[PDB]
Length: 108
Ligand code: HEC
Image 1 (cartoon, rainbow, N blue to C red):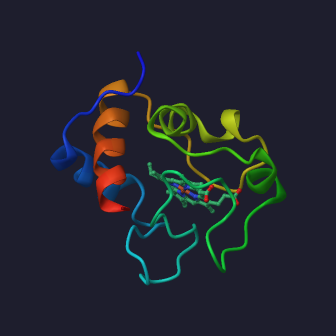
Image 2: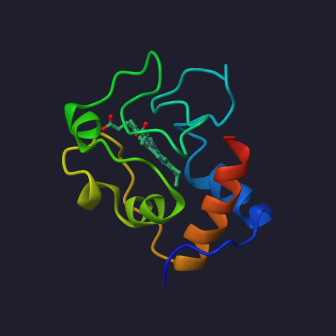
């Protein structure tokens, strides 16, 4: 089904184990392998200031929302072929819902 709000508490733990290596959620957090995710919802892809994206991510020009984030995170490379994000996906719908619930709040 489409995105449905889950547990931000569980989502935070999922973010720590699966995403934190490469991403911060905080404005003015450290630079990492992946782009700062602050403000990502409601922005187009390829727009984080200072970050060096692939042409693939920029050209996709997706306007991020919770539903297309869930599709992306299921399998990033299927959604954006040629992306350099070395992440194979969140296979479980409940994990995507929980993670995205956290991420939407944590990046606001
Ligand atoms: C490093 C090994 C990473 C892990 C683990 C995750 N991400 Fe990532 N992400 C990474 C890179 C190098 C990039 C840039 C890709 C490119 O082709 O330029 C990304 C990109 C994203 C994006 C898109 C951002 C945009 O501005 O369009 C999102 C939304 C994103 N990453 C989220 C994300 C989440 C939620 C993760 C855990 C589930 C995750 N990433 C893991 C590198 C890495």
